[PDB]
Structure formats: C-alpha cells, structure tokens
Image 1 (tube, rainbow over the protein chains, first blue to last red):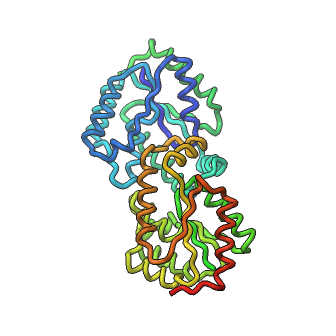
Image 2: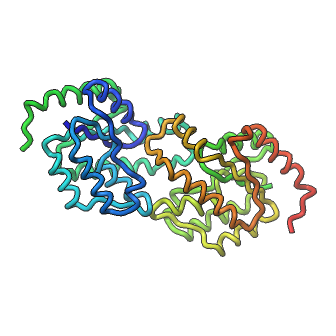
Image 3: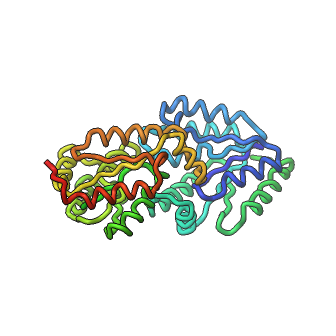
Length: 172
Length: 172
C-alpha cells in the first residue's frame, strides 16, 4: 500500500508518519520538492511519477500538496489536470490518501505556541479552504482526520487497520 | 527615535523588540502587512507612509522586509524605488534601521529545533542573500547584529546606547 499524507503544518503529519512507519514497516519519503517545483513543470511531473511507482511506503506530502502551495509561491510549478489523473491512475489501486487537518483557530494557536513571526493570521484560512478544495476534486478516495479531535495515536491506529485490511479491498 | 527592525525569523527580533520597548519606553508596531501587501501597491504605500510619521516607537519589519518577501509570494505588492526613497526621506533624521540575522546553517538549526515541516533547506540562503541585497541598496544608514555571535541582551544594549546618543547625532 502507498500511504499518502496531506495537510497543513502543525497537524502531527510527521508524528503520524513515524508511527505508521514503525508499525507497518514502510519507509518514509517527502513528496513536496520546493527546489524541483521551481525548475519546471516537466521535471516536477517526472518527480511525482517516480514516486508513483514506489509502494509499501509513506509519502509526506504528494501532488495534492503541490496543487496547493503552488497558488502561493512565485515561480512554482503545478501539475495539470491531465497529469494529475495520470498519476492518480497509476496509484488508484495501491493508494490511501490521508488528509490531516484542524480548525483555523486551533492551527494559529499551535503556530503561536511554536513561535512564528511571519504568522499571517488569515492566510491559514485560505490554505485550509484551498486544501479541502483540492481534496474535493480528487480522483482517488480520500480519508481525513481532525487532529483537533483525535490524537496522533488514534489516527495512526485507524490507518494501520485500513492498510492491513486492503487485502479485502477491490478498487473499481 | 524611530527604531526599525528587519531580518529573518529565528533571530530573536521579537525578543530584542520587547527589551528595547521596556527600556526606551517605545511602543511596538508590526510593519509588514500580508493583508495589505496583497490588496494593492497604492494602499500598501499609504500604509508605510502612515508609519513613517510615528516616532519614538519600534517597528518590527518595515519597507525593507516587504522589498524581500515580495519576491516570494504571489499577489504581493512591492514599493517602487521612488516610493522607498520617499519614505526613507521622511525618516532619514529619526531612523535607526536594525538588521538582525545569523548564518544559514544556524537558522536552519533553529528552525529544526522549532519543528518546521515546510522547511525548504536552501530557500533560507536566498532569503538571507536577498536581505543583505536590500540592505545594501538602502538610502539610510543601517546597523546589523549577528544573532549567532551576540545575545539578544547585548544587542538591545548596543541599540539602547545609540538611541540615547542621538541627541549628538546630525544626519546630513
């Protein structure tokens, strides 16, 4: 199974990743490539394509993340709808898209707790509004957990159970 | 005296500001305006112009900061060279431009210590390379402190001494 993790900062994405790795015994890879997302759309698509072949691993931020942070940074490539559906097709059978989020208020609170200085104050709202926009236009099925209601542990357990239950799952 | 603080995160800018305020009895104002830096160049210029009138205060990030973060975020206005020199002219006599920075390696280390997930890994290099680029093209005189060599306390003392010494300072 190719577990994909998406969502904004301060949602324990890295923690949940660690737990899933230790448990499911899957390596961890960071999809998002600020460097490559600048160079060009081609080398960017190639990149995500290489990852689309891997399996039995966890990807911390994939195409969906790029389809979000691209609408924020200058000189930042984005995948075309055709390129997306292409990648989703190659992973449709081995993919578990995970979206970890939290309320805007909660995220700013965690951000303040961490000590940010550039902390906009509303840009988060947009990021969140943007994420659920991208997830809504996904070709694959998506799973989301509110990191404000469930702990990093309870979440990893849910996913762990699904993954091990895939043997009975037929993607059609 | 108008104290203007510029530089990247993780350089104790907010801490140096707190001390300067407690001592010099100057209120603190955050220059940068994400909201207004998006709206438009006009309302943005009107913003800094309004701040260029205040005195005996500390501004956490001002025009120089905008002249940096603008080359990074989409839909982000920037001040024109004429608009900058205009503002620098209005403050040339009452301004102390402070630049707090640190080595790229040190900043990433502090970033890691804080727990960032979007932490590029080289974008900082650009930000720093960009800042010293802007500071170099400044109309006012600038003062910079390496937050990697001097403590937040020693820095605030240096500035505090300068400010109180302005009575003897003639800007020409």
